[PDB]
Length: 126
Length: 126
Ligand code: HEC
Ligand code: HEC
Image (cartoon, rainbow over all chains, first blue to last red; front, side, top):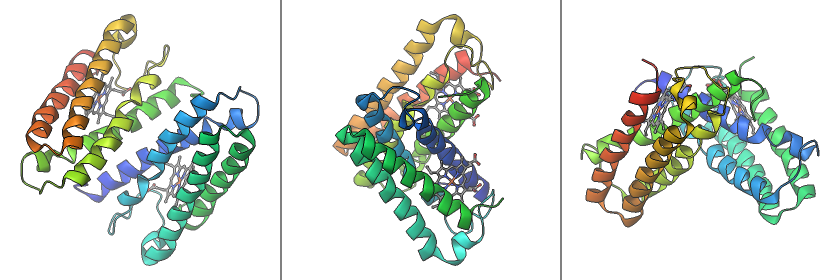
């Protein structure tokens, strides 16, 4: 859906920005600094699930640019493992949110955050 | 979820960018320049439905900035009518996509596009 590489870059950066907001806005809830409303969190994690599937299709071959490292494309299998693993961490978060289980939510939230960082360490420029 | 107005601005601009891509990428399909795969379009419109609900919460009071016109906030009811009308145009598009009905898809796609423009004409700076 991208006329030029720059359009793929803009798309993925926007998708990742929205992910970061839908993830990060739960930090006060996880920490107990804001109240836990199970329905609110269930709905928010549903949005995050949808968003978390979006960036990867905008790293199609030849879409070097932005702060993407070239290693994304020199080993397509390893990058795919990282995004699939990330999305399965999001599945655990969804399951916790759907269950209304704050303890499971906290644990899953930490694992999701670790998975964001694991990808950045390998694939995002400083 | 926004520490400063700038964070709301960045969020809504990213959400609108993603909407524009999920909407605009169907133009060749509507025009018959690309093939119509009912399942592909159903899935894409589901994504668009989710995204189309997101920008509005990031025009909270005091989040003037970007290319948002101040009229968004001086008549909250009228802005809300426009975004709700837009989302109901998206509902028609969803219904068409879910039905696998290309004629209804075309018609709904045109009405959605008109609704984007109607809001821009009133509420987006040149
Ligand atoms: C690889 C499988 C990634 C996972 C998982 C996550 N992110 Fe990431 N992110 C990745 C790359 C390669 C890039 C650079 C994209 C580019 O072309 O520039 C990024 C970037 C971001 C950004 C900045 C977006 C922007 O506005 O330019 C943010 C805010 C971001 N990423 C956040 C984020 C969070 C919170 C994640 C887990 C919930 C996450 N990313 C996962 C690669 C990957
Ligand atoms: C009002 C109810 C709107 C509807 C419906 C749509 N858009 Fe719009 N859009 C609106 C505003 C007020 C703004 C400015 C936001 C800001 O603070 O700068 C915009 C902006 C866009 C953009 C630019 C985003 C960016 O990268 O800065 C795009 C690409 C865009 N809008 C597209 C778009 C499409 C395709 C719509 C219908 C499917 C649509 N918008 C609806 C207000 C409203």
